[PDB]
Image (tube, rainbow, N blue to C red):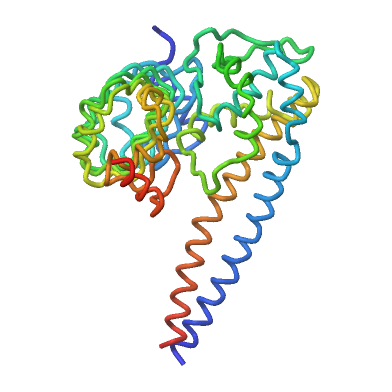
């Protein structure tokens, strides 16, 4: 609402980093801008050519747009935004390894399947209420690390989330900051 | 004679990586110890506080970050809070509304703090905490903490101590893995 321009924020961001190149940086820390970075402009972001990590955390981001013109993006982290739908991630889908998106308002996991090479998906204290989304998430062949503590589903579950998580997805190695255990797998076998 | 020179060179890389490992353990110990030495002493003086000030509330947030529970987002219910005598005006996400009323009344408050998972990467939280690290020197300085209250300072020593420990554990794993790999290459070169 005329709060933070991506160019205005990038201007301070590039000046604060004091880096000669506006698209040389692997880690483009645009986090916690003030007033907060509302909606991200794709033409501006396109610049970031060498950026492996793009931290736009803790701002007032409502939508995810302009995956296009992103080459080497490995760890996209848009946590504590106001984001509702995981969409417009087809052009980063080739590279994207980790989608850190905690404390959003992500109710549905519809559009996460485009992420083919996604290794680590942290979406904690989100709005995921049914395990229906987990079946859609199961398409991910390389998904190792998940974080689903604080979601509205794990509240209604009425059992150990660590155990109930591991049993839900066989692919997942780490679930809510745990490691794949022999005792946990046996407990998952006793549950199912 | 070739395999000897190889074993020596790698055995030098062992010693460097051991010293890095040795520097981090102390630095981890130093921090976690202060957290564990506080005990319920400060936790009791918070439970007594009941209606705390807008300075010590932020100090609870830094702790609430590590719990990963009901954390408030966005520039909503936020304003500006005066520091000491100097009429300074700053922009911050502001305390929880009702996250503390639920954290407080939980008797396990002590149990939740006293125990933390080791080798916790917490990239989700450190991204959310990044805003508070650049501002660290303004509010979260010890000399502004102890002034707000003695407990507060311990909790701001509590919150920071974990941030240090985490950073040390995040220097341990990589520089100790590169050690453990090198160590393996030397052992093979010695056998050869």
The C terminus of chain B: image quadrant: bottom left
A185 horizontally vs B96: left or right: left
Q: Is residue A74 above or below residue B174?
A: above
Q: Is residue A130 above or below residue B51?
A: below
Q: Quadrant of residue A79?
A: top left
The residue sitting at the front extreme is A190
Q: Position of residue B92 (x, y in %)?
A: 57, 17
The residue sitting at the bottom extreme is B1
Image point (37%, 19%), residue name: A61
Q: Quadrant of residue A11?
A: top left
Q: Position of residue B163 (x, y in %)?
A: 60, 39
Q: How many marks?
A: 0
Tell me, yes or no, if residue A51 can be seen here: no
Q: Is residue B50 above or below residue A178?
A: above
Tell me, yes or no, if residue A180 can be seen here: yes
Camera-nearest residue between B117 and B14: B117
Q: Position of residue B141 (x, y in %)?
A: 72, 29
């Amino acid at each position: 609402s005329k709060g933070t321009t991506c160019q205005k924020a990038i201007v301070n961001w590039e000046a604060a980093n004091p880096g000669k190149n506006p698209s040389e940086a692997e880690e483009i820390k645009l986090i916690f801008q003030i007033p907060p970075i509302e909606k991200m402009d794709g033409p501006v972001l396109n610049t970031l050519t060498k950026c492996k990590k793009l931290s736009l955390s803790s701002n007032s981001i409502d939508k995810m747009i302009s995956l296009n013109m992103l080459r080497n993006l490995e760890i996209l982290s848009l946590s504590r935004n106001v984001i509702k739908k995981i969409s417009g991630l087809e052009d980063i889908g080739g590279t994207l390894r980790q989608l850190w998106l905690s404390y959003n308002f992500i109710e549905k996991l519809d559009g996460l399947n485009n992420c083919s090479v996604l290794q680590t998906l942290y979406i904690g204290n989100n709005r995921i209420k049914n395990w229906e989304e987990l079946d859609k998430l199961k398409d991910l062949p390389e998904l190792e690390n998940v974080l689903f503590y604080g979601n509205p589903i794990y509240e209604q579950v009425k059992e150990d989330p660590k155990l109930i998580v591991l049993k839900k997805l066989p692919t997942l190695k780490n679930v809510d900051g745990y490691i794949i255990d022999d005792s946990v797998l046996e407990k998952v076998k006793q549950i199912a | 004679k070739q395999c000897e020179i190889q074993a020596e060179q790698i055995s030098k890389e062992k010693e460097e990586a051991e010293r890095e490992l040795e520097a981090a353990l102390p630095a981890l110990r130093r921090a976690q110890e202060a957290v564990d030495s506080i005990e319920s002493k400060d936790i009791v003086e918070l439970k007594a506080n009941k209606k705390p000030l807008d300075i010590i509330k932020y100090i609870m947030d830094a702790v609430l970050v590590f719990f990963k529970a009901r954390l408030i987002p966005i520039q909503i219910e936020e304003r500006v809070f005066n520091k000491k005598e100097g009429k300074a005006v700053l922009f911050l996400k502001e305390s929880y509304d009702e996250s503390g009323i639920q954290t407080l009344g939980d008797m396990n408050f002590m149990k939740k703090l006293k125990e933390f998972e080791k080798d916790s990467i917490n990239e989700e939280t450190i991204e959310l905490l990044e805003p508070y690290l650049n501002q660290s020197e303004d509010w979260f300085n010890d000399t502004f903490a102890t002034k707000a209250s003695k407990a507060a300072a311990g909790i701001l020593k509590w919150a920071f101590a974990i941030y240090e420990y985490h950073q040390k554990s995040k220097i341990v794993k990589p520089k100790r893995i590169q050690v453990a790999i090198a160590e393996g290459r030397q052992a093979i070169a010695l056998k050869e």
